[PDB]
Every structure is written in C-alpha cells, then in structure tokens.
Amino acid sequence: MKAVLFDIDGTILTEEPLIMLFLPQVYDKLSRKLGISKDEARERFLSEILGRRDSYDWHDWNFFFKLFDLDLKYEELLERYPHKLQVYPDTIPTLEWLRDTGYKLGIVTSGPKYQRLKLKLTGLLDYFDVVITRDDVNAIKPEPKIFLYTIERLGVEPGEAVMVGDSLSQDVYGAKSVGMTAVWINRNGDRGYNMADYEIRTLYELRKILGGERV
Ligand SMILES: [Mg+2]
Image 1 (cartoon, rainbow, N blue to C red):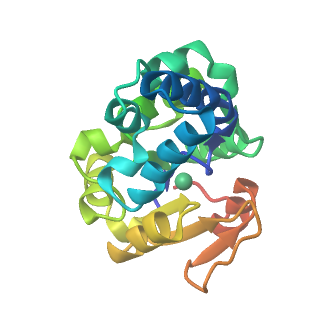
Image 2: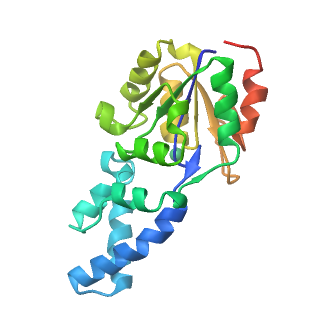
C-alpha cells in the first residue's frame, strides 16, 4: 500500500459541537426574518436539509444559509469558534505514524472549500499531501472523479490506496467502485451491511490492518 485517503467529518474530527452552537442562531435569525416561531423555523430549516439528502448541495452549510437568505457564512463561524471542532484522540497519532512510515496522505470530502479551513483550524492540514473537496472537482462522493483525481495527484494507482471514512455510500462504495481498498470507521456501533474490506472502531486499528513496514 502507498496511500491512505481520509474522509473528514465523523472520521478524523467532528463539528457537532459547532452545529449545536449555531443551529439556535439559525432558528433565531430565520424566525425573525419570516415572522414565525423558532420551532417553525427549525422545522423549515431541518426539512430542507433532509429534503436535499444525497445531493450536491447537502454537504454545504452555506447552501442552506443562502437558500434562506440568512446573514451567516460558515467560514466566519469556523474562524470564530474553532474550539467547537473536535479532533478525535486517535487521529493525530495515526496521521503521524502514516506520514512517518512514508504513506501519501489525502483528504477526499464531499464538503466544500471550507473543509480545508476546518483542517487548518484544527492543526491537521499539514499532514496531508493533498486535500480534495467538492469545490476542487465539482463533484461529490461517490462520484469516481473525486477519488480518481485525488490518487492522480498523489501519484499512485487505485489498488495502492486505502480509503477510510464513516459513510457506507460515499466512502466505502465510492472507494471500492474505483478499485481501492475500503475501510469503514464505525464509531457509534452502526450496521455495516457486510460491505467494507475492514471495519474499525478507531483509527488506531489501521496499524493492525496495514502493518508497520515502510512504504
Ligand atoms: Mg463523514
């Protein structure tokens, strides 16, 4: 193996604390704008998100801010509250080990350009040889282009790369469809449907899967 590719959200970090912080502000701003209750604003906002699942726009918070013409920019929220982004304890030792061992490291995310800002703010950016977001290829997982462009940039063949992510449809199916090895990270004890080549609970388990020999 020569390269390990990572999903971001739910895989190497979580933005859930930031989501918990800004959603009430969204409900506040939306209810005040539309002259409706905060509960009705919540219903409308969340319904729109659910309605656009599995689509290009689903992975972009700014899409939803813009759709409701709200005075919010996710980049500004990120820069203001970077401590609300939480890096999993198993992330940095794993990236350190992989980089030191000689693996090329890539990010493949269906989120937009601010995903790179999230990596910068959490101190993870510099571990990666390349970071590919939706906005870099005009495509989302599991479209083959987003995986193929990433490994092309890394200079490796698909069979020389492993994808690690928490989404069965985006990460596992996406990676396998272009000939990569697929590792599903399952932090919350969900159902895996017998799909991935390997299933792990934390990134520390990658050491058992890959072994320790330099590449
Ligand atoms: Mg994810």
